[PDB]
Image (cartoon, coloured by chain):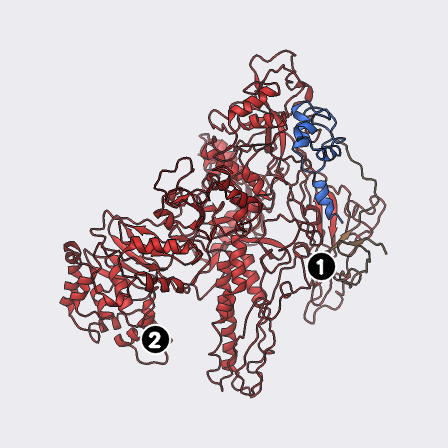
Chain colours: A red, B blue, C brown
Amino acid sequence: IPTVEEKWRLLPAFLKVKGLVKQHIDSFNYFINVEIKKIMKANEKVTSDADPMWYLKYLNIYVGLPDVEESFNVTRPVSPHECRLRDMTYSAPITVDIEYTRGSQRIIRNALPIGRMPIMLRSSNCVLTGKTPAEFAKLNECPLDPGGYFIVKGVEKVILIQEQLSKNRIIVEADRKGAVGASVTSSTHEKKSRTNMAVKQGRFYLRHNTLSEDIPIVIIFKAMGVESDQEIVQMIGTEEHVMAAFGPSLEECQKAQIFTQMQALKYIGNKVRRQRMWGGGPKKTKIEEARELLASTILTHVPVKEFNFRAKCIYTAVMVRRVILAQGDNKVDDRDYYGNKRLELAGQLLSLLFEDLFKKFNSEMKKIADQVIPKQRAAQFDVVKHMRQDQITNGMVNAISTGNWSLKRFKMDRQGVTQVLSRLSYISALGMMTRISSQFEKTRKVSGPRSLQPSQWGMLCPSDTPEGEACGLVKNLALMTHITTDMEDGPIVKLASNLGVEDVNLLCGEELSYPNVFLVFLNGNILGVIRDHKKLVNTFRLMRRAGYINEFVSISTNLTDRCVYISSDGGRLCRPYIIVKKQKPAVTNKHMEELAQGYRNFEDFLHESLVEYLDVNEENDCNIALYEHTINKDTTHLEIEPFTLLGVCAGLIPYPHHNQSPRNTYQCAMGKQAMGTIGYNQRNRIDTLMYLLAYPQKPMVKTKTIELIEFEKLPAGQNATVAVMSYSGYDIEDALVLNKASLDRGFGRCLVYKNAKCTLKRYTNQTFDKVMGPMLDAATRKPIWRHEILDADGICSPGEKVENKQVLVNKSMPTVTQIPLEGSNVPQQPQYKDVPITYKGATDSYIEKVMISSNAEDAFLIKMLLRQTRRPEIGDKFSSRHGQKGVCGLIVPQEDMPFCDSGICPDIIMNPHGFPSRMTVGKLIELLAGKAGVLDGRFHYGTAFGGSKVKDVCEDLVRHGYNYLGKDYVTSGITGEPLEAYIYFGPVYYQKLKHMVLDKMHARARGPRAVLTRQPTEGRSRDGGLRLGEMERDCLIGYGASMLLLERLMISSDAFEVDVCGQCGLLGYSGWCHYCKSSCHVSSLRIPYACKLLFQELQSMNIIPRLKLSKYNE
Amino acid sequence: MIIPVRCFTCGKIVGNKWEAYLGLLQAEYTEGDALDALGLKRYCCRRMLLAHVDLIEKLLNYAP
Amino acid sequence: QPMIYICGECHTENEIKSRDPIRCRECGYRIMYKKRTKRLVVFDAR
């Protein structure tokens, strides 16, 4: 109805088909769908070199879907449970039919698995799409899981999204010294780096991918002959400065010599470094200037794809003119600009791996074919020998698991991509998803690309930063920001040939002409001539805006340079925007009664020029407006809503207005791990740190973006009555006097689970198979606290407080006690060195579930729900929704806490010392809309850039009997009379984080220095406790007291007075050294075993062994 | 998961008052007035019902 | 001899002993949840 409601109810309109996570699933859907067939187009067709041509030919490779549909879970259909318990993996075989060009003519077209696709959970092939929260029972899973993460041997592995810069694009930087035209192109294959440079005082050369040295450009232009060097100079430019500056290079070339192509190019014919592959050029003895020019078809190595070299000529001649930035000292082009950074995404990496694994398998098939010639049999290519099937399985799973997309064709052995979903709630289950990870940033500690550039207002969150090392380097793609995969360049080629974009083979170096705006970059691909940018661009927009070409094809019109791009390639961010129609937003204030109830079915606001999709570039053209209320009549697009730069994990604060930026960074880190209700699965599943609560409460000052997450059905923190009050010296630096009698009445339980996995192996020769079962059953504890609490069968114990290093499970462990060769005969399982699985911490767990989850191999797991209800104590972690992370200072009893007049006494207590220097005024308000929303029954909103102001809330508090300001009138329990100054109150929403003081119980009894690795108890694997590393002993030695330092030395790890010297003596006895008992060479010197290990390990690597003593006395 | 029997900071008994609202949200008072016909005249128990998520039903949907 | 093998997918019990991997009667269903036991565990009710 109003002017406003339309633009704030476009959210459930687009958040269904392409929303907040669904870019992951969209990309991988396409990559299952068609791009695998695309890679199939790289058919075999070469395999029979020494053969009567028995080529294979993939008829149609689909992900289990050539002629088939139900091949999408080919382990006898299996849910994600039966993949998160049995630890199995999703699997759909990438089946295919093959077209033997067989000389025995049996063209066999059986559907052959080629491996297995690890299907992204909830893709358009999984069994969890198009199903209701009732159908989500037989599949054991929530309806509202994020979805989009893989199944890696029972471990949820998401794929972080990288930020790799654009291909096909010049990068004309400006060093403090000189200009750099570095066109780092590609062909989906390799990082080819055909960079130009302003090398030596006006001297231009090409650090090509290979070429042995720096090649003067004018000779390069000769290599694509434009030999009339007049044409070189006129093409580069026509003004004074350009001609003069370029002059030196032509002068140097001519002074060398001016020849055509058949000479002066042997000057580069032999000067080529890809000549380094003399052995890689076995046939075609034809190798010199003319022949690296024959192989100069690949000396494209750039987007422009011609055989007559005029395209590469003009590319170099716009390179050479956009490196001389007309005295390129004032002109600067910056790297970190999200029109340049194009997101390669989980699916894209999987597409690289599709390509490379099919090509690797085809290469090994080719090798087998090229060795099988002596075989006079039919199985030169047959399916039976074609038997790497289901081993692309291992490649894919290794890639997704180890995080290694190890490659050869693409020049990247990337490690560090895939991670495990931090299922501490569903808040961090999303925050883990929808995360973008940075890239090279040449010196990552050079903080240029660390501050948030203004160049993605919208598309990346402002406040989602993990303070520390990954600040500004791991990024939450946190909202409405839709994403593009790829297009077809054809139906822009047609509109270029039509719309007034000439063919560049009709003109020469007129291209310094200001009417002739002549960037036409169809995705880097070459260029288009014709003038009239301000008509081509505008009619192209107003043609896609009316049902034609797909609304993603952004086009920038910059005037500093003659920039008119057509970027229709992948990695592009996006956003929706309301079309202003240059006078008034085209939603007409009455689309609501279509935006909500009946029709305009939806996304049909994209087929009507009503709301449209931008990029970064097109945002660099347009002129947006925040609200309608302040449109000024020159605006091209309109903001749907302000609150979607603050995104899914970051739009959890109430009133994120008023906080600082640091405070919202703190909160949007803390809120992730905070103990919460994982959802609906919880009990049916098994997983490590299921940090539940037991009595959680919905937020109560909520945000319109808390609803949209659906994760306000699953709130992560208790909703706590709270004062603002200073009790007695324990509160002080963000500490909390949480009263007992609310810990008692259940405020903030925990249900810390953990997980023991008795991976009961099997072995080839000897067997674990039958050997299960302790229960010796002696007298004391049937038998003993070794095997006291297991069961009849020693496996399970669903409900018994198994305590402090009892047995959770044991197994006699005969693994290889029989030697696999003809070894000892007697070890037919009397040789069990039993390996107990026992450990625990200093409190009782309670075995709650026992699992015999056994995959197809009998490799018995024992999954176990070791639940430990560690309710809080002095030291536990709180957060606040405002990066206000206090800790329980005291724990007071009920009767001492202040009571207002009604009878309310705090649960939590803060002191008003976290606010005035952090300035979270988003908390003095949350306690207004709590106490005003409950005292009235309401359920309030403070939403980013909207909310509910202070005046209406104040009047609500008035109506149910309190201040405008909600400041109660408290008397003090301790003494029994009114506090002198009033006391803030009302509901807060305290989250209860992980990282308590019970998971952090650690201490060390003794540390010696061992002999095995000759180490003290360093860090973990020996005990918990300390680790005096670099800065720690740096402080230790920096004291200023002599034998305080001496004591630290004498007690460091060990000070054994072993006997060793130089004069016929070594590391041996003292009284009578069997090494050398000369009886005059007894030393008994204090020394840690580390120096002795140095002695040993340097015996192999010879070095001067000085050894001597001196008198302590006079 | 289930209803706190006591208002963590009040004392009042609560768990007796969840199968009345699911019968007083269909007499269709405003929540603020389904929680005045049952006694809750303070902050506390208003939180302890208005804010709680009965995961009991949805969890038990597939318990076995 | 005990029957401690429920199946969240076949609500029935086998305890077919070792060298018989899991199979819940007539199916794979290798997702045994094992029954609780009959010891009178004591809880501080606090």
Could you tell whether A630 is left or right of A975 in the image?
left
Residue A746 position, x and y percent, is 70, 31
Image mark 2: chain: A
Q: For numbered disc 1, what is the local secondary structure? A: loop
Q: Is residue A82 depicted above or below A306 in this figure? A: above
Residue for point 82% across, 58% down: C14
Is B42 placed above or below A768 here?
Answer: above
Identify residue for label 2. A278
Q: Quadrant of residue B54?
A: top right
- Same subunit, labels 2 and 1: the answer reads yes
In the picture, the quarter occupied by the C terminus of chain A is top left
In primary-sequence order, the first of circles 2 and 1 is 2
Query: Would you say B48 lies left or right of A382 here?
Result: right
Q: Secondary structure at mark 2?
A: helix
Which of the 4 image quadrants contains residue A698?
top right
> Residue A687: x percent and y percent?
66, 49
Per the model, the C-alpha gap separating discs 2 and 1 is 55 Å
For label 1, the residue is A854
Q: Amino acid at mark 2?
A: Trp
Out of C30 and B1, give the one closest to the viewer.
B1
x and y percent of residue A477 in the render?
48, 47
Answer whether residue A176 is visible to the viewer in this image. Answer: yes
Q: Chain of mark 1?
A: A
Q: Position of residue A545 (x, y in %)?
A: 42, 53
* Whether residue A162 is situated above or below residue A11 in the rendered picture: below
